[PDB]
Image (cartoon, rainbow over the protein chains, first blue to last red):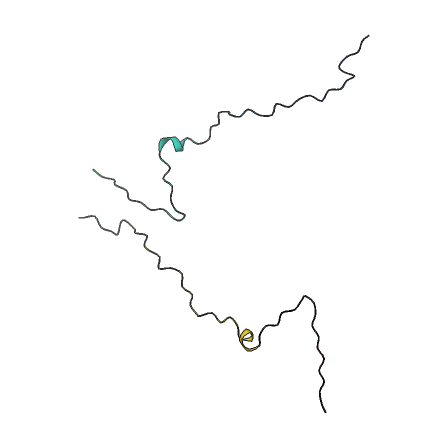
Length: 50
Length: 50
């Protein structure tokens, strides 16, 4: 009955990603500092009693 | 009784990296001076006898 959009097959458009979603990631990094060190086995001292 | 340095297992220090023997590189390079050529075979003629 008339000219439509169906005959003019449109490709569309892309809206890929959102830049900042909330990710679980890592909890531990929140409770204690990172203490970065040199490669190799790490050793420290443990004070136990009172 | 007291706080020893045995419980606290110490790491230590690195002297370095020493090579056992002196390097025995070459002898052909000292007796006959290297005469470099292009890639490919080499060939020479020898005229012997009188």
